[PDB]
Length: 57
Image (cartoon, rainbow, N blue to C red; front, side, top):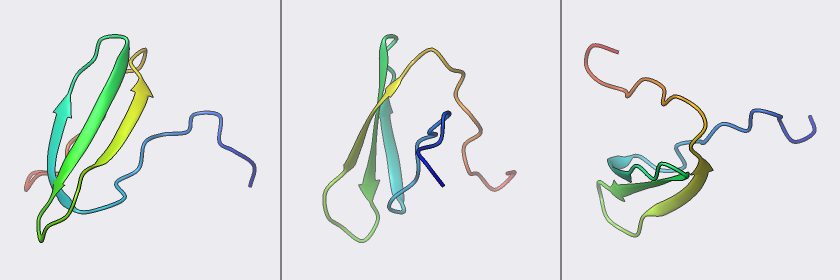
Protein backbone atom coordinates (compact mmCIF):
# COMPACT_ATOMS: atom_id res chain seq x y z
CA UNK A 1 0.00 0.00 0.00
CA UNK A 2 2.67 2.54 -1.09
CA UNK A 3 1.94 5.20 -3.77
CA UNK A 4 0.77 3.35 -6.92
CA UNK A 5 3.07 3.61 -9.91
CA UNK A 6 0.22 4.25 -12.33
CA UNK A 7 -1.52 6.63 -9.92
CA UNK A 8 -4.70 6.95 -11.94
CA UNK A 9 -6.98 9.97 -11.43
CA UNK A 10 -9.99 9.43 -9.18
CA UNK A 11 -13.54 10.79 -9.18
CA UNK A 12 -13.56 12.54 -5.81
CA UNK A 13 -17.08 13.93 -6.33
CA UNK A 14 -20.05 13.13 -8.56
CA UNK A 15 -20.90 15.88 -11.01
CA UNK A 16 -20.79 17.12 -14.59
CA UNK A 17 -17.27 16.52 -15.87
CA UNK A 18 -15.84 19.70 -17.44
CA UNK A 19 -12.47 18.53 -18.76
CA UNK A 20 -10.14 20.64 -20.91
CA UNK A 21 -7.57 18.47 -22.68
CA UNK A 22 -4.04 19.83 -22.34
CA UNK A 23 -1.75 17.99 -24.73
CA UNK A 24 1.18 18.31 -22.18
CA UNK A 25 -0.80 17.99 -18.87
CA UNK A 26 -4.46 16.98 -18.84
CA UNK A 27 -6.59 19.33 -16.73
CA UNK A 28 -9.78 17.75 -15.37
CA UNK A 29 -12.64 19.52 -13.60
CA UNK A 30 -16.12 18.30 -12.64
CA UNK A 31 -19.04 20.63 -11.90
CA UNK A 32 -20.85 19.24 -8.82
CA UNK A 33 -24.47 18.29 -9.40
CA UNK A 34 -25.86 19.48 -6.06
CA UNK A 35 -23.40 22.38 -5.92
CA UNK A 36 -19.98 23.51 -4.81
CA UNK A 37 -16.60 23.96 -6.48
CA UNK A 38 -14.67 21.83 -8.98
CA UNK A 39 -11.95 19.38 -7.99
CA UNK A 40 -9.01 20.03 -10.31
CA UNK A 41 -6.54 17.39 -11.51
CA UNK A 42 -3.33 18.25 -13.37
CA UNK A 43 -2.41 14.85 -14.81
CA UNK A 44 0.19 13.78 -17.36
CA UNK A 45 -1.05 13.63 -20.96
CA UNK A 46 1.21 10.79 -22.15
CA UNK A 47 -1.58 8.25 -21.60
CA UNK A 48 -4.82 7.48 -23.48
CA UNK A 49 -8.04 8.51 -21.75
CA UNK A 50 -10.28 5.76 -20.37
CA UNK A 51 -14.02 5.19 -20.74
CA UNK A 52 -16.58 7.73 -19.56
CA UNK A 53 -19.39 6.45 -17.34
CA UNK A 54 -22.48 6.52 -19.57
CA UNK A 55 -25.73 4.58 -19.85
CA UNK A 56 -23.92 2.15 -22.16
CA UNK A 57 -20.97 1.75 -19.75
